[PDB]
Length: 150
Ligand SMILES: CC(C)(C)c1ccc(N2CCN(S(=O)(=O)Nc3ccc(SCCC(=O)Nc4ccccc4)cc3C(=O)O)CC2)cc1
Ligand SMILES: c1ccc(-c2ccccc2)cc1
Image 1 (cartoon, rainbow, N blue to C red):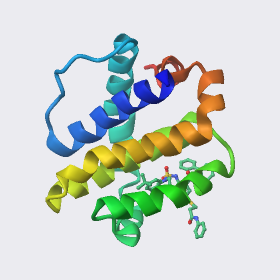
Image 2 (cartoon, rainbow, N blue to C red; image 1 turned 90 degrees about the horizontal axis):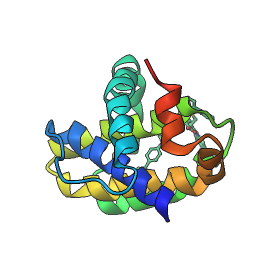
Image 3 (cartoon, protein in one colour; image 1 turned 45 degrees about the horizontal axis):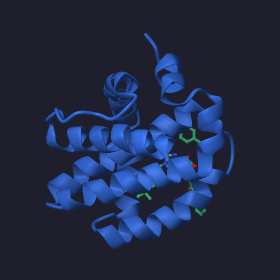
């Protein structure tokens, strides 16, 4: 599925870039022009959310204590249910991705870099399994870039 593949492309690249401090220069797939604009957006908005909500993110990180792939697996099963409840908006979706980047930075600190790709997959699974129809209706990643346009 195309939407899953493009979402994972953006989400995995943003989480790994936040954790390592280096950009991925490997080519993107079809819709690469949109994925580059989505990453430019996440570098502005996602970095901003992590800074402005640092104390809440630290509290959530400390309580969840994600330190391995099994932790990511267990948490993704419950978060598919939690993320399905309540209103859907681009603010909620960028906060999920921003929290993923916050966790990815912590995983690099505890020498668990190998857990960033499964984390990006679970973030993508949570997002696409619960919001597929909303994402499609809101013009997908083009809609995301348009909503946060400066
Ligand atoms: C990849 C994986 C490791 C699986 C993963 C996936 C998701 C997350 N979650 C969820 C998404 N957020 S959010 O900040 O985007 N958004 C939220 C943050 C907070 C809240 S307040 C209410 C949560 C609560 O206390 N429920 C609660 C408390 C006790 C019992 C039952 C329910 C709700 C949301 C929201 O979107 O529903 C971050 C934390 C973490 C890790
Ligand atoms: C239900 C619906 C939306 C949110 C939410 C909104 C903004 C940022 C993070 C989560 C939480 C619970």
